[PDB]
Length: 300
Image 1 (cartoon, rainbow, N blue to C red):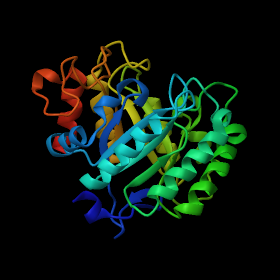
Image 2 (image 1 turned 30 degrees about the horizontal axis):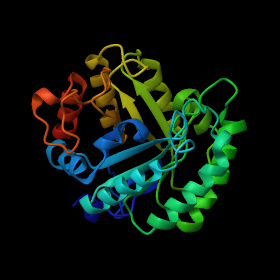
Image 3 (image 1 turned 45 degrees about the vertical axis):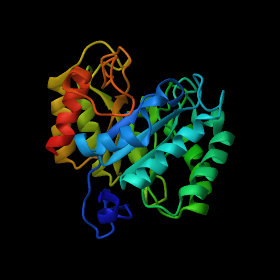
Image 4 (image 1 turned 90 degrees about the vertical axis):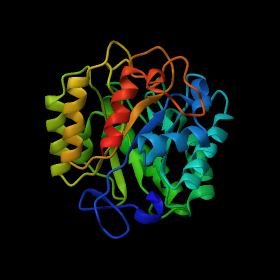
């Protein structure tokens, strides 16, 4: 129903819109690393998220390093499984080239190009796909102008040769926080968005104001990863500040994916150790974070 109704997404005046030009807001879940917790990514778990949580997007977090794709490329086939499940479920899907310790996207740029060529050739004639080309550039030696923007200007043409206009999400500096610099030096492609990531354990008032600065430059922002925890993914759940962010995203019509769908014993994990990898969770099988996120998507 979702993808049939909204169909082809695009950016108009800095906003995510559907094929009839109406604003649309995506809300869903990210997997954790597909090399560690891939068992939670399958048609049945995604169907349960769609029907019980109300998700309309799912993010496949394919780590590049940390035992991910560069070390063992077999994980690309789990991405394919997730994309095909989203197509069958009629929801959107984010293909996330999940850089992190490999903090400069240029480190594995050749592999990224080849990977995005393959994925855009396979799936580029579906409206479901959103390409996230560099999860979290980070480090003081990785800047928008010098590192990230030129990387995107190599990867985006590869995608565009196969898929002229599905959304592309481009990471920003300082773990996808520095939307100010991107918004002042935007990419040319009209269907680009810039990633902004937050963690509710950080006091967020200035980060909200920086998001607003970026939006005021006409840049489109996708909150492609956020957590209820601290920036490590652990250290408590911070629901008061999470709710502030939720309300801010709704007011600004910002799409989002929560980190993350796993039973790992960390505060940002949505599931408890028990939880069936094929869905059907009881309340007891959701973590404090997962219960909250589920409520947010259901109330939407």
